[PDB]
Structures are given as structure tokens and as C-alpha cells.
Amino acid sequence: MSEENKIGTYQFVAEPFHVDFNGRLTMGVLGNHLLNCAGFHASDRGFGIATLNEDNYTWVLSRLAIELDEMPYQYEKFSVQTWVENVYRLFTDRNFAVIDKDGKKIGYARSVWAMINLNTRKPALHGGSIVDYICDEPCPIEKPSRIKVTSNQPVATLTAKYSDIDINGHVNSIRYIEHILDLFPIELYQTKRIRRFEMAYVAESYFGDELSFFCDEVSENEFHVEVKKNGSEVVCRSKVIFE
Amino acid sequence: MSEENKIGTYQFVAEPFHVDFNGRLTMGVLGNHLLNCAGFHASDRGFGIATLNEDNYTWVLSRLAIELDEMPYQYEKFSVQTWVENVYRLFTDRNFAVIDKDGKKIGYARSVWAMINLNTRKPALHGGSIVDYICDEPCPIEKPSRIKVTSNQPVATLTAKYSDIDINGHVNSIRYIEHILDLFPIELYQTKRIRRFEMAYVAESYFGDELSFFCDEVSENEFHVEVKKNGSEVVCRSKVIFE
Ligand SMILES: [Ca+2]
Ligand SMILES: [Ca+2]
Ligand SMILES: [Cl-]
Ligand SMILES: [Cl-]
Ligand SMILES: [Cl-]
Ligand SMILES: [Cl-]
Ligand SMILES: [Cl-]
Ligand SMILES: [Cl-]
């Protein structure tokens, strides 16, 4: 199997309820597409959640970094390519390219997934098919790493609601993205765009939990965000770079 | 052209970030699919927003009623059929059927759209193609009509945020659905399901507006909701029937 053959490619159109006030695809919706594509790619090749679950493992998303030159516009076609870059002992690195209507690469993403035993919730091989799909396609963006947040004064608070919760009873990955991006003043979105966005998923939140949001502005364009539940426990961290 | 030939049919899969804690497609996501399907159907046949806009008209959604026996489950295929039932002088009635993975009709929807002149914002014929697609397919649910809400004590308040706003700078149709459905206690969603849901879109809200929510519980299972902006102006009304 060729290197090109290990890549999954998926076609989309930017719908009106999935774009912002500038008509560009929202980060939350892009994240949704990336994670669904990861799932299509894994499931079609027999190394997705369903297969893992039969042997008492599952996949958990640990880190996501998205870097963009531009975002698709309302009603434009776009596509996502995804592939497995590495399968390490404790984590798998899955990468993405986003392709605009003209076939130009307009962004990239890197995701880091843990495999955990479902009985013990403990972390984490080759009887499977995943190793066969390790692919050398380039993804020329910096790997996501630990995010530091110094502030201990919350800037906003929000209770987890029915619309936030997925089938496992927790606040879903994408809903955290939406809430974080709602922290920023509209003048920022009017004058700049997000060029890099990172999520670190630390712990779970449930319906009724009070989420508090803390933010360090490290430069004019770089913000580090920490979300905590019920005061003290970090549930996720984020880095947002505007330009 | 046969009656069957005037129907558009669109295929979907219920994605994980589009279902609730019981694994069923959310109302907001279903609404999103219905409205997008309406758009696919109109645009493909030359009576959509794009065509209207060339002559200084547009379509505005006035009313939506959805009635369901069940909702698709996570990862199931489903489909939406849509067709034009009537083209009246001031409004067009567009209807929908929702079809489950087995081909069983599991719900219906009715939508009412106004055509308005874009210069004058005034309301509202045959040089177009729409009349050619009037279709007698059955949609055996009650038409939506005016919703009465008596309560003048708000039960909740929310500021319109970046994630709420569409390309025209207003709070989008689907975001109102999500916020309304977040008013109800989780015990209701644990023990009952929404069998009928109606929206009436009265006026627009913008970024930063304070939305207040008023609710009459007319019986154990029927709720009427009014959303107002900045205290006084009604922006939408809703009816939610659980069973
Ligand atoms: Ca989840
Ligand atoms: Ca709109
Ligand atoms: Cl989209
Ligand atoms: Cl699988
Ligand atoms: Cl981190
Ligand atoms: Cl869906
Ligand atoms: Cl059109
Ligand atoms: Cl009404």
C-alpha cells in the first residue's frame, strides 16, 4: 500500500449555521469535522473505538492543535485529509490537512490520542491493523505541548447544560471550544483571525457542573486559557493565537 | 414531472457531537438538517435565496413545527425528504418527512416562509420555477400557528455571544432552539422525549443583546416559551410537548 493510500479524504460544504459573522467556518465546526474524519478513517480500517472496545480498550483525545492560513467560506466546498503519523506505546499521533475549494492546503491539524483499558482506566500494539497505516505525509506545524496558565482570577463562569452533554454524560470536546472562543471580544474577531488554536483535554465535566474560565494574555495576540470545574479541578486548557 | 419527482431526499448519519446524553439526535441538529435540506432543494431548482436576491427579494423563516415518534440514534443512517406543499401570495409552506435507517417514517415537519422585498423590508409569483414543484405528498401533522405566552416573569437570562451569530449578524435560528431546550430539567429528558416542537421567529437579536426567557407550563407535558431581547421585545416563541 502506497503512502497516498493510507490517507483518508473527506468532502464537505460550509453550511450557514456553521459559519461566524464573517461567513467563515467556526473553529468548533472544524474540530467536529476533524474528529469525525479521524473516526471514519479508523473505523473503515478496523482500528477505531468499536474494534478497541471488543477487547476492553478505548481511545481518548488528549491534545488537538489546528493551524490555519484561512478558513472555508459559507457555501464553499472543502475537504479534510487525515492519516496516522505515529503509533507510540502510550499515544497515537493523527494528523490532518484542510484543503480549500481550489485544492490549496489552507491548514493543518495534529491530534494526540491515548489508548486506555476500560476496566482499570489505566493507559495502554500489533495484532491490530493500525501499524499498517503509519504514513509519512507532511504536516508542517508545531506539535501541541503542555499549556501553562498562571492567572487564578476567573474571567467568566458557565453551568454545563443539556446542549453541552454527549452520550457518555460529559461535556463534549467541541462544546469546550465554543465556550472558550466566546470569551474573546467581538472587536478581535472583527479585526483579526485565529491562526493557531490548541486544546488539552484534562478531565471530564458533567451536567450541572460550574465551569470557570481563567485567562493569561501572554502577548497582544496570544492567550492561554484554563477551564476548571467546581472551583478547583482543571478540565481543559487552550491556547489561542490571533493575527 | 411526477409527484415523487418533486421531492428532494437527503442522506445523513447521526454523529457523536450531534446527539444528546441518551444518544439521540438533538432537536437543534435536526432543525439544522431540515433547513439545509430546504436550501438544497430550492437552490437546485432555482427558487432559493440566490435566485430571489437577484431580483431584490429573499426568504425568511417564520414558523417551524417538528413532530416525531422517535429520533435517530448515534451512528445510524437517516434521511430527510422535503417538498413544497403550497405557494401562497404571502407565504410558502415547505414540508418534511424524516426516515429512519429501516426506511420507516419516524417524523414530519412543516415550515412557513415569507418572501420579502430587500429594499423596503416589505412582504411579497410565477416567472419563477417554484410553482412547478408544488407537491401533494402527505404530511399528517397539525400546522403550526400563533403561540400564546402569559407569564411575564423570566425564568432565565442569557447574553448573545460570538457562537450564536450568523453571517447576517443575528442570532441564528438553531441557536434559539438550543437555548430554549436548555431551560428544561434533565429529569424530563431522562424520563420523557419531545414529541412536538414548534418555533415562531418574530424578530432578530444581535451580539451582546440580553435574551430573557419566559415560560407557561400549560399541562404537565406542554410548555410555551417566549424569548425577549433587552427586556421588552419578543424575538421568538416556542411550544414544546413532551411524552
Ligand atoms: Ca465525549
Ligand atoms: Ca440567520
Ligand atoms: Cl459545515
Ligand atoms: Cl472500528
Ligand atoms: Cl496541558
Ligand atoms: Cl448529524
Ligand atoms: Cl437559488
Ligand atoms: Cl407566534
Image: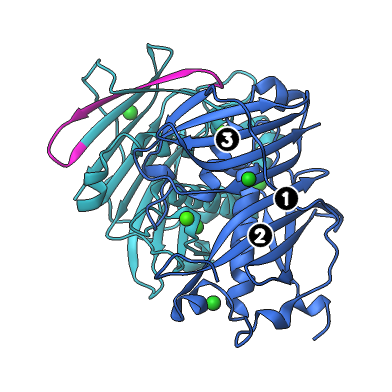
Chain colours: A cyan, B blue
| Chain ID at mark 3 | B
Q: Are marks 2 and 3 on the same chain?
A: yes
Q: Are marks 1 and 2 on the same chain?
A: yes
Q: Amino acid at mark 3?
A: Glu
Q: Are marks 3 and 1 on the same chain?
A: yes
Between B105 and B214, the one lying in front of the other is B214
Between A54 and B43, the one lying in front of the other is B43
Binning the other alpha carbons within 10 Å of mark 2 as few (below 14), some (14 to 19) or many (20 upward) gives many
Residue A108 counted in the magenta span: no
Numbered disc 2: secondary structure? strand
Mark 2–mark 3 distance (CA, rounded to whole Å): 19 Å
Looking at the image, do the residues carrying marks 2 and 3 touch, with CB atoms under 8 Å apart?
no
Query: Which portion, as a residue range, is magenta?
Result: A206-222
Q: Amino acid at mark 1?
A: Pro
Binning the other alpha carbons within 10 Å of mark 1 as few (below 14), some (14 to 19) or many (20 upward) gives some
Q: How many marks?
A: 3
Numbered disc 1: secondary structure? loop
Looking at the image, do the residues carrying marks 1 and 2 touch, with CB atoms under 8 Å apart?
yes
Q: Amino acid at mark 2?
A: Val
Q: Residue at x 62, y 31 (%)?
A: A57
Mark 1–mark 2 distance (CA, rounded to whole Å): 9 Å
Q: Is residue A44 visible?
A: yes
Residue that numbered label 2 is attached to: B112
| Chain ID at mark 2 | B
When asked about the image quadrant of residue A229, the answer is top left
Q: Residue furthest left?
A: A219
Residue that numbered label 3 is attached to: B226
Residue that numbered label 1 is attached to: B144
Residue A194 falls left or right of residue A16: left
Q: Residue at x 74, y 59 (%)?
A: B79
